Length: 49
Length: 48
Image (cartoon, rainbow over all chains, first blue to last red; front, side, top):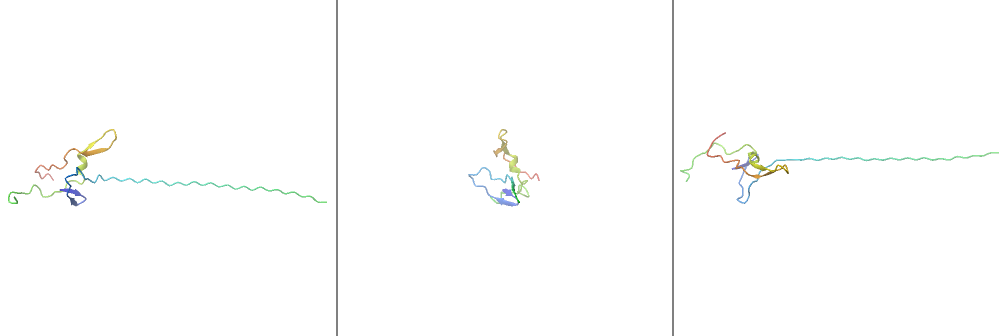
């Protein structure tokens, strides 16, 4: 008799162990990059007579 | 024979992963390794 949760199971003769070994990972990343630029250049020239 | 058979205990269920207690252990990789101790030799006993 083998159990996982409350379910019961039969093990094939070929298999040494089937067991839950119940492990979990979560890996998360979030990334942001931002870049901004603004350039303004002007000229003014005048004459009168 | 079903006439010779008798109950060994009221239940068949172990603690839910008793299996992992009988595994081997590789110190240098850090990991568990396959089934070394028989975790479930009930031994005709009803230790509950």
